[PDB]
Each structure stands twice: as C-alpha cells, then as structure tokens.
Length: 105
Ligand SMILES: CCc1c(-c2csc(N3CCN(Cc4cn(CC(N)=O)nn4)CC3)n2)[nH]c(C)c1C(C)=O
Picture 1 (cartoon, rainbow, N blue to C red):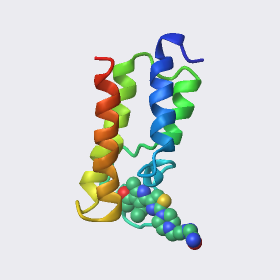
Picture 2 (cartoon, rainbow, N blue to C red; picture 1 turned 30 degrees about the vertical axis):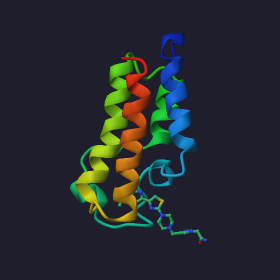
Picture 3 (cartoon, rainbow, N blue to C red; picture 1 turned 90 degrees about the vertical axis):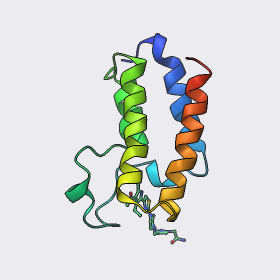
C-alpha cells in the first residue's frame, strides 16, 4: 500500500479530482464516447488509474506520480484542440497541478 511519505500526492490528486475542470480526466478516455483515441495516444492516463495505483503502493516516488499527472495533460494537448472544451480543461488542470506541486518543491 501507499507509503505515508506520498500522502501529499494523495491529497493533490483528491483536490484535482474535485476541480470543476477535472471532469474530462476522472476516468480513462472512454471508447464509448470518442473514437480513435488509443490510435494516437500510446500511454493513456487518468485520475482514477492514478488514485488506485497510488493507494495500492504502485508509485515509489513523488516524481513518478507527477510524471503520470503531466501525462494526463500532455495526452490532452496532443489529442485535443487548444480551444476545445477538453483542451481548455487540460490547460486549467496543468496550471492547478503545477501550482500545488510548487508549494512542495
Ligand atoms: C471528449 C472525450 C474526452 C474526455 C471525456 C471524459 S467524459 C466525456 N464526456 C462525457 C459524456 N458526454 C456526453 C454526456 C453528457 N451527459 C450528461 C447529460 N445531461 O446527459 N452524459 N453523457 C460526452 C463527453 N468526455 N476526456 C478526455 C481527456 C477526452 C479526450 C478526447 O481527450
């Protein structure tokens, strides 16, 4: 299970999941709702996957956790136009995360 040294990561993820711009990223990108995603995006990532991985002890380091958070936003800007609703949400959430991360590093 999760080492207590990563509790601050657990809290950042909780706060991201609560954010009103987080809705595109709560669960894996869903083939029932969009086609051609994994055709382009070789490493999908979403907050639920991160939440379960963190809780079961699947992250060793905060940097590994942060890399997955940035992967969410990088995938978003790869697939989505910047002025689309999801594309804008990714930019908001990247700002939100980088701000929380800077409080610690
Ligand atoms: C656009 C796909 C995408 C999502 C995403 C997550 S979730 C979601 N969608 C939720 C369901 N809606 C329709 C709908 C509305 N309602 C409520 C009602 N009042 O009916 N129910 N279904 C359509 C879009 N898209 N995330 C990412 C990162 C994406 C991409 C391409 O990168």
